[PDB]
Length: 85
Length: 84
Length: 88
Ligand SMILES: [K+]
Image (cartoon, rainbow over all chains, first blue to last red; front, side, top):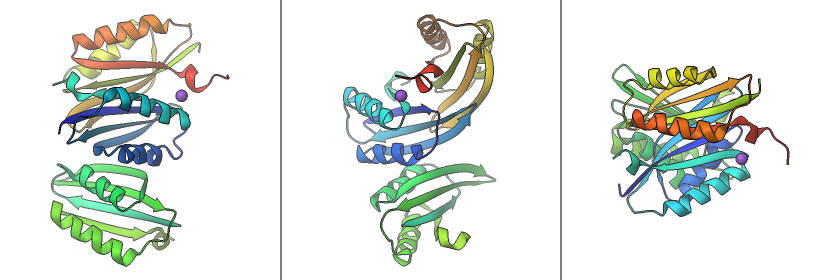
């Protein structure tokens, strides 16, 4: 990997979220290394670890996921894995 | 238009989620839902996939089977029709 | 209740994390309505939905959770549930 990141998705409705977010990840040419989804209280929640063999622009990715999350009524965060290693 | 269940079984999950979800996307299929478990000496995953276009299950079964061999896992794809 | 939030945690190692984070939530006088944890690739992750019957200050909580997170080498995010409910 040149890039790795953890993506967090929080919303109220689960409907179509896994398809939307996985499709977006794929649109951006990122690999899904792992994924998990959990209903928690009244919320549907989803986390994915993603990567690419090329350096990416987190400024762009963060804004792009944020804007995409908004279209689906969910909050999306992306964190570079560089924080841990 | 198309809906299916993909089941994956192998001994080691290293790289399996990326490989299989990557193959799914290469084939233009949507991942509607996904789950994984470690089971005995095995890792398993399942995904429900779909497309707005008709698909050829004959081709897909063969393609996922061949792809599975490259990763040392067994991949089945079954149409949603069969779980009727 | 008057406050509800979703807390998310990411780090490399699970050792001590559940105890540290649940312990911090109780110190802050917050209720855990629900919780879940998973290993995800090489990371330990947990998520919790918390609430209080008193209004809270998310400016303070965000800072406090991030600061506490650092003591445990984990990234802690908190999001008010109001964002998913409120009209505009
Ligand atoms: K939102």
